[PDB]
Image 1 (cartoon, rainbow, N blue to C red):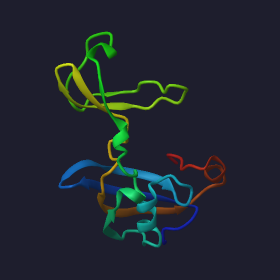
Image 2 (image 1 turned 180 degrees about the vertical axis):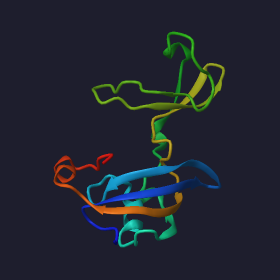
Image 3 (image 1 turned 135 degrees about the vertical axis):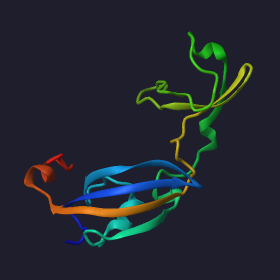
Image 4 (image 1 turned 180 degrees about the horizontal axis):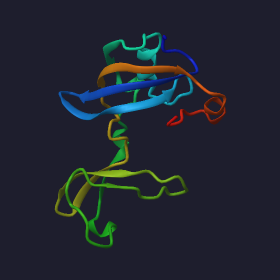
Length: 151
């Protein structure tokens, strides 16, 4: 059948950003309930079961723009222990009032250590290769729960 609202869709995908493959796998999702990034859903909407295709998803319809205000230099002492002074390092530091914001080292040149509280894909455009494996109708529980079940 055709991918549409309230259908439980199983896709196998390859995610590539600016050249390299950052992710790849297979998942199931309830279509129409904001379970996927907007861009991605729009591209799947209408697709036939089995249909394969590619999709360019702008940061705007994915994980959003990069907020440079999200970058910041912090003292090594900020982290009272022994960890990493290298990029890629991600921490889940707490927000000044609530609802923590995971950060990521952007560099380390001595004491001046850069960090990023933006999504690791913020500011990036995503290029997907998709394959609609299974497309079934959602069950009452799924609809109530708002998510697809391993079933």
